[PDB]
Image (cartoon, coloured by chain):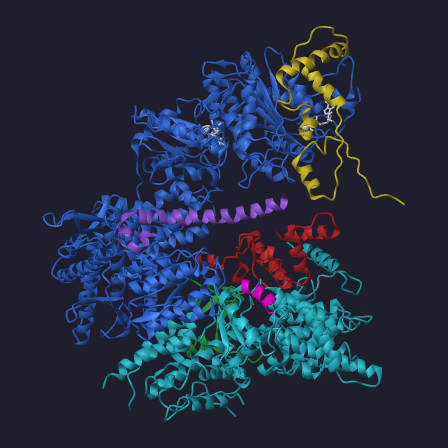
Amino acid sequence: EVENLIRTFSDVNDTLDMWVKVQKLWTSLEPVFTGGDIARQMPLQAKQ
Amino acid sequence: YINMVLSTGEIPNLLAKDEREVWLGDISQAYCKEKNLGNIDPPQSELWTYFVDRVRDNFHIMLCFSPVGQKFRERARKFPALFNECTIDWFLPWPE
Amino acid sequence: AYLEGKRKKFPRFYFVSNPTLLKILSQGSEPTSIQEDFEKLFDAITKVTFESAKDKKNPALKQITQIQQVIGRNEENISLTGYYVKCEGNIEDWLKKLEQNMQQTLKDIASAAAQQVFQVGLKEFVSSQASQIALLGLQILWTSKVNEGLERLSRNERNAMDIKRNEIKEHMNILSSMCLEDLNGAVERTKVETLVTIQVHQKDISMDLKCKDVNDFEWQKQTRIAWKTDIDECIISITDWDSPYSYEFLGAKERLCITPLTDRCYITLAQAMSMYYGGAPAGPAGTGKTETVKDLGRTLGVFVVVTNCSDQHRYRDMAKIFKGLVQSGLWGCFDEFNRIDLEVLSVVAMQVESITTARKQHMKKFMFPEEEIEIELIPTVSYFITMNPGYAGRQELPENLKVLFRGVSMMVPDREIIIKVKLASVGYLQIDLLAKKFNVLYRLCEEQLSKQRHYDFGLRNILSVLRTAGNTKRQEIKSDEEMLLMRSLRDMNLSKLVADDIPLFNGLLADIFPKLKEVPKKLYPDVEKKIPEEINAESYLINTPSFQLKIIQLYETCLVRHGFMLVGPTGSGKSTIMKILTEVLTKLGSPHKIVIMNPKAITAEQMYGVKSEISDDWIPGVFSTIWAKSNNRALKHTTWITCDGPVDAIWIENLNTVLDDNKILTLANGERIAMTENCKVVFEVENLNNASPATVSRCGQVYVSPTDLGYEAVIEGWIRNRKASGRAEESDKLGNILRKYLINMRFIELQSKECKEPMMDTSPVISVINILNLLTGCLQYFVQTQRTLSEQEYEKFIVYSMAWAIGGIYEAQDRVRFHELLLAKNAPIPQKGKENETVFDYYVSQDYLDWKICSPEEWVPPQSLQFSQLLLPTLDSFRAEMLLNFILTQPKSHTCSNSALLIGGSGTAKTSSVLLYCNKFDPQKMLFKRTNFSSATSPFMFQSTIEAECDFKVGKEFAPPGNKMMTIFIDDMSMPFVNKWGDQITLELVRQLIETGGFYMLDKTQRGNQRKMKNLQYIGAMNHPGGGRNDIPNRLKRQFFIFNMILPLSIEGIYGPI
Amino acid sequence: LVRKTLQDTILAIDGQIIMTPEILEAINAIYDAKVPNSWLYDPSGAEISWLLPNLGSWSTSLSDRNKQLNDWLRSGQRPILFWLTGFFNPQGFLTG
Amino acid sequence: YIKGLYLEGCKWSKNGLDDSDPKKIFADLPILHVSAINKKMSNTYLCPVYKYPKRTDKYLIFRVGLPCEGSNNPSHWKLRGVALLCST
Amino acid sequence: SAIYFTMIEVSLVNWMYNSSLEQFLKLFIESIDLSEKAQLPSNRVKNIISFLTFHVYRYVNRGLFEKDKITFILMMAFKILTTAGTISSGDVSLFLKSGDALDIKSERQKQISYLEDNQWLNILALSKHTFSGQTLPFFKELPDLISRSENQWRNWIDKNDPENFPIPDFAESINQEKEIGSFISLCLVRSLRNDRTLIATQNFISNVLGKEFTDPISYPIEGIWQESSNMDPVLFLLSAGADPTSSIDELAKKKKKFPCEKVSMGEGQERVARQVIMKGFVEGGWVILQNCHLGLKFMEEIETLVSPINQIHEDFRLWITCEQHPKFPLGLLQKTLKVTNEPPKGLKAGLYKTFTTIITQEFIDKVDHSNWRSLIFTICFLHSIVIERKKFGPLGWCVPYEYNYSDLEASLLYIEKYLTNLMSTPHNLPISMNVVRYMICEVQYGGRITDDLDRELFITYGETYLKDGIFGNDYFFYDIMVDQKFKYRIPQNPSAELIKYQEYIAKVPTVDNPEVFGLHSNADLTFRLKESKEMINTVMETRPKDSSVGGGKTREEIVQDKAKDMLKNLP
Ligand SMILES: Nc1ncnc2c1ncn2[C@@H]1O[C@H](COP(=O)(O)OP(=O)(O)OP(=O)(O)O)[C@@H](O)[C@H]1O
Ligand SMILES: Nc1ncnc2c1ncn2[C@@H]1O[C@H](COP(=O)(O)OP(=O)(O)O)[C@@H](O)[C@H]1O
Ligand SMILES: [Mg+2]
Ligand SMILES: [Mg+2]
């Protein structure tokens, strides 16, 4: 049970460590490309 | 607190105001007898002053400090009538 | 990578943070949105006008048609007369277009002014032109006048330079007589002041030039701006280094006074730039290294990007700035660059070394370290490091950096030159003479006078004098310049000075100004007639010249300042000067109220109000609610919010915004209460010791020394008060006797010499106040019976009242010396006694009047006895009972507060002798409450007990149960914690409560309203100071009558009956 | 300041008082004939007494300096030949 | 009439400043008579009187004009490091 | 054991000096093996002791700056004598103090004209000191002997070399004691004629440790590489204005490593250094780390990286170069081979360093006029003379400003700009307006200068060196009687050759007369005194705080007796 819980919490950490990061990245870039003027340019980086 | 207790004889706002009258009720029968057999019902301000003096007479505070500790010297300066008001018996190093 | 791609198109972006760039590029479409961030991109272009343009074809496209620099409410506006900036879609292309058209307009405007300045007056020119081009125009004029002067010396036309110097003086008289016109706005003031900071330096130089040719080095040294018609471009020469003007719109910026050091610093900084080495001026803090580098930039019309360097700066953060400077072609001083971590500077060195090597070879492009591509270098780059040797920050720079930067050691700027400029800036001629005098005085008086805390003879007080010395020059121009300054020096400092230092000052003032025989003061004939008239209302007030003088001096400061404070020792007559002045001003039009509070008595959080930790609701502040009540324009009330307690760094900091010229009180909840004309702030501080030198210079301090209201005046008043009590014959006789021992012979001065080690250190006035109290208390019997006595019967009572008031504080050894001194001066004493017999044993009896040995009342065994709770009548208890009776039976007065502290050794029967006195009180007629103080006891602990013990109320006033006249014994009064500032917080509440008879309620609901207890007496008992035990505040000592309890010589009388 | 420190240094070695940080420094200095930094500079950093390296020479000056002040103060008349060294503020004397 | 100032680098030989005697550092100066002139040059050495031998700008008291008339320039004394020490 | 506890005394002087016990044991073990093998057991022991002392002194002396080189060998000499009964702690204590505790008021009157007031209190201290293994004070009745009308004592103090000549009245009894006699003959010279203490100590060290200790070692870089292994790096302690990186590459050419990796340590240079050192580790090659004191975090990591646990090639040698830094990682100092590269700080050695380095043949051909080469020498000659003034202390410069070569480069770069503008214009001398030249060379150097009276001094040097008559051949700055007399000219070159300037700098004397700086002959007695007071002050800090001094009086009891003797003299 403990070894399975350790394995669980190891995979939880790997997920949650990645989550907070992806959020912060997303939180940084959410205003730029949703915003019109930068997104008017960089058609390739807008589609992504 | 034990300084305050030793000098005053009483802590301010220690016990509830309703709990005074219960305590002072039991105290009264000794008080009337002790004061040259007065045998009149005391007021609750004149009953306290006896109870406080009754506390001090009965309540002893043995302190047990170390003279080498740096706090000991500070506590004497910081708390008056914790050193002055209680008899200091000094423990010398053991003889042969 | 796209951001770095835009950054490279408009370099100045390098100096903005990534969020702000992303905001600007995202809002590139709507150019009104960018308007907030203009002040980060460029220098002194705070706001931009946006016209409608192309309103016929391709509409809703705005066009920029003027550059604004906004200082406070006023602006400097340079309109783009042609070269309009039509603002296209792409922000970084129209922003480049704006920086291009900025310069191209200034070049056009400056070109047409450097032509106009020759064929137009200097008063006429400077008004028409924008700050930056008036400065540039004035500089162009002067360097033409010198050149042309020296050119004519080389051809041998004699007195050709003397003719040009005379013009240069006219040019300077114009600029000083434009400081006298007080033109509106902060822009035109900063425009005319910067012109004057230049033209004193222009005059100073060309007054002692002495060059027989233009090419002679003493002229080449000088900073010279000239408009070359051949290359049609302004060129600024320093030594051999001829830079063109950069044409950055600087607007109206404050210029530092140009010292002979600063001129020699400018040459070094120029020689560095010519050789392509960096510059790095290194001096102590306050020399303005940053400001002198900026001043050179503003002289060349180039933007200087300041970057406040710190530990948090990395090698990447620094590399971004340097990639901005090189690509832009702007200078870039680094304020406090030493404070950068040494790790960083090793990497920055390779960045600066890579920039240097590119500038030396004249490379159009070079590869920066950690950059893949070669970046464009503008030739007119520079980079400066304002360091600090004797560093407060980190160790000296690396070995690589030292090579790259040419230092300038910058001394502290000569004070005389600062003053000289500032006197010119005001509107004085012969600045050189005055500025020498004015310096000499303040430099000398600082050394000669006593080093007291309220004395400031640094630049803070100097600049304060010159604005008040200026306001006086504008109004009376015809008046002599020396006498106006001499007068404005005098009237401000005289108030501050202690009694000992007034003859020293007036001497220095008569040393440095021997031409000026006498200067007339501001008469103030309305108020001067009221003070005598007002004083003779109250029976107890005596009017001395030295007291009337200090009332006037408080009124002089009350008119100009809004934060005037009243310094002086205890019993100096500060509170009474306040009360008199207000009672005078009441009778001359508008009424004047005083609201006494103690800021120390209450916690900082509880005075100003703070956010409650429970229920998240705002509790009103005590001061805020007094301030808000006090600041209303209704029925010309003009209240004075006085702060009796001592000033400390903690509580004045919150109130610091009120004292300053802003005059708005911030509670730090987003509420800012404006100060009305009518309301004023006062401080009845004793010392002013533990207060910052800044907060002192804001307020206008009047000092009241001990000798202004002498104890002789207090005694003379007390006797005046007896005659108004209906008992003139008594007072007449008590006069003859009081004068004989107190003023005729200085007995308190003679006693204090002969008797050593007084157990409590009291002032001579305190001792006299206590005499007059105890002398009352003795004769209070004979008032009731209307019994006048002889001069023998009073002369016994007075020497008793003297003995205990003056010599009570003395221990047994000194009591004998004190009694031996009464035998020398032939006072009435007990003729006969035993060995070690003193005056202190005896007293003067009411029944029959003579000296009687004070034997204690015979003991009556209290039925059943316990040695532990058995207190007997003793000689020491009797004397204590007797003295306590005299102070506590008295009616409250000006001298007495009905309160009697008794000092004495550990276990000397202080606490006992009070408890012996506090029995035999009729429970109906008097009450008694004992509150033992300790190091823990805070003012809220003490305030909560007294508030609970007297709840009965007569209207507004509070009282003890029924109307008993409770006597509040405070055992171990000294114990409460003395803080770093040396001020006992809980005792400043005790003092407030004895003096004013109240404090301010601290229940959330009701704040800024006083609770006033009607009938309270106060006993205290404390172990006498010294040996790491707390002394009571000097201020509080004056309220209490003080006597020393001594261990008995024989305890036979005490323990013999037991 | 000297009087205070010297007395405490005689007490501190005998064990009458605890060794303060200033008194330990003063005892170290006096052994190696250097002036205790307490006497040369105050906590703030301002100069309080003349800067001589050796203790012996510092102590002769204290006697010589004090003598010129005392012989001026006690006697009415001022010295014919002033010892400019002997003043704490010689710049202040000359302005005098 | 100030007394007990010591010339470092130089001696006083009553014909103005003179070269120091071998192995005799800090030669004592005679009684200096200081006054005020009331304001209102070559071959007169404007020597600095220092509080200590350390000589920093803090321990500068004042400057004293020392004649140096015969066969030695004032600039030759500045290089020799001539200065009047109170302390040593 | 003595020597190692000297190395712990040296740790207190400077943080960079501290060496491990584990580094000492290598020297101690090596000193047994390398020593001469004797058949007699006492001769074998004698042979190890001689070899040990030197072999460790050699090792320690290498990682010591020139100011603290003579201080260490004096500590080592006391630490050897303090173990035997020859010197006590009170004896060592005297030499350092020597009656600077005594005050003239309490003690005897001087009585003698020729002694200074300090020289007399120094006498008095000897008169009251019993030394070690003697009944009564050795020097009791010295103040009687010197007070006697004997010119022998006046002559001995007045001598140039007092420490080399025998003591006029006490010589005969000093020769009888061999072990202590050398130390009491030093204490006399510290007392009377203090200035000759550094020279008097050499005489003493040579009679305690042997001649080999007074002689200069001057370690070449080939020796520093031969001493070093792959696992133990070579730390260089850099005094300001020194760079050994060139001297490594010079040795690297002979060892076929010349194109070696170099890495200026800083922020984000850790990732570069790792990549560089991992190549060096396997491939082989030298790795010079510069300004290492700045990048402290890597210096903790490099200790564990260059450990034997990681595979290192035998060829690979690591070279660290860093200026002294407090809170340097101790661990590395205890592994590294510590060397100090300090400038030789003479006038010749100064001039040599500028003409070998920053002046090149390219440089002296930049303007292409006689009057540029003439001026190049005068600015470079002035440069050295302004540096070597700092030796003489507060007489030299009120405040000592380290005048870098940047000040020389700038002042020269200026003269190019100035002369090129006069070269452009049509005895073939340019105008060279020296009024300007003065000011600008007293603006490039004036950058450092904070003091107003130090400024006025430099300004004055300008007026003596950069006068109009330097361009003429028959001008010679200062023609001093140094050795008959050296001329101190501007060397004349028909054709501009760097060799002919370097050739003349050979002929310049090593021992700089004080007359070259415009000072008096007595300036060296003020210099010598300062560097000897500095030696005594550095060895005073190292002294142990042990109460057991010897002679039946503790450290605290000596302080007590003084503190009581002061209190009665207070007013
Ligand atoms: N002009 C006067 N004539 C006579 N008595 C005076 C006069 N002015 C003040 N006094 C009296 O002298 C005492 C001075 O107290 P006052 O409060 O005026 O001074 P203070 O300096 O504010 O005292 P503190 O600050 O210590 O409370 C009081 O007894 C007061 O009534
Ligand atoms: N009149 C008296 N009768 C009996 N005991 C007394 C009397 N006066 C003082 N003492 C005793 O002397 C001591 C004095 O201490 P205390 O009364 O607490 O005063 P203090 O404030 O000086 O400590 C107590 O132990 C008290 O019992
Ligand atoms: Mg008052
Ligand atoms: Mg008590």
Can residue A18 be seen in this snapshot? Answer: yes
Write down the colour of chain B.
yellow
Residue F383, x across and y down, in percent: 44, 78
Write down the colour of chain F.
cyan
Vertical order, B15 against F436 (above or below): above
Vertical order, C382 against B48 (above or below): below
Residue situated in front as seen by the camera: C774 or C101 = C101
Give the magenta-colored segment's residue range: F297-306
Q: What is the quadrant of residue F340 in the picture?
A: bottom right
At a point 65% along the width and 76% down the height, the residue shown is F59
Magenta stretch: helix, strand or loop mostly: helix
Residue situated in front as seen by the camera: E36 or C296 = C296
Q: What is the quadrant of residue C584 in the picture?
A: top left
Write down the colour of chain D.
red
At a point 79% along the width and 38% down the height, the residue shown is B90
Identify the chain drawn in blue.
C
Residue situated in front as seen by the camera: C965 or C72 = C72
Can residue F124 be seen in this snapshot? Answer: no
Write down the colour of chain E.
green
